[PDB]
Amino acid sequence: SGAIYVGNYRVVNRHLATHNDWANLVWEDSSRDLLVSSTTAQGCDTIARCDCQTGVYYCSSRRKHYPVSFSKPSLIFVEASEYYPARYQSHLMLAVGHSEPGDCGGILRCQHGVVGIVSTGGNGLVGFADVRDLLWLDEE
Ligand SMILES: CN(C)C(=O)Cn1ncc2ccccc21
Ligand SMILES: [Zn+2]
């Protein structure tokens, strides 16, 4: 579990979105595993605006933050998990590291702020859903 809180937005994995998220929907995209809902209070997070390929991510299944190198957001085939069939996911970054299903929502961060959230795992990789292209998160 985990979310990004930027302005009056809550950014979550689409597959972990609550009824309250869907009832306050701003934008969702299954291919990215992202959903954004509206909040009443303002959030503490800053979104990175950059093409960094190094950062640090939170792994709940280890209670640890790990420094990683990661690929640029791409369209990638993801094998079946407890929450999705095998499919193509877009805007996905991969790194070498530990990821189980419950790790989804952990933040990946660089020197510029939040890059994305854990969205995939298995076979020694962790996949992150990028948010740095979503420039509208920074306003309105
Ligand atoms: C201000 N908002 C919410 C948006 O632009 C949301 N958004 N983000 C990407 C994207 C792709 C097509 C259509 C809407 C999309
Ligand atoms: Zn950066």
Image (cartoon, rainbow, N blue to C red):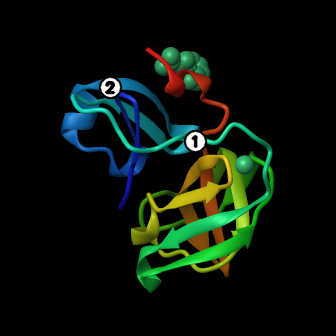
Left or right: 48 with respect to 137?
Answer: right
Q: Position of residue 85 (x, y in %)?
A: 52, 58
Query: Where, by quadrant of the figure, is residue 99 drawn?
Result: bottom right
Q: Quadrant of the N terminus?
A: bottom left
Residue 32 image label:
1
- What residue is at 39 percent from the left and 44 percent from the top? 44
Residue under pointer 2: 25
Image: 80 above or below 93: below
Check disc 2 and report its element: helix, strand or loop.
strand
- What residue is at 66 percent from the left and 47 percent from the top? 112
Left or right: 26 with respect to 132?
Answer: left
Q: Position of residue 59 (x, y in %)?
A: 49, 74
Give the amino acid at mark 2. Answer: Leu
Give the amino acid at mark 1. Answer: Arg
- What residue is at 59 percent from the left and 40 percent from the top? 131
Image: 88 above or below 95: above
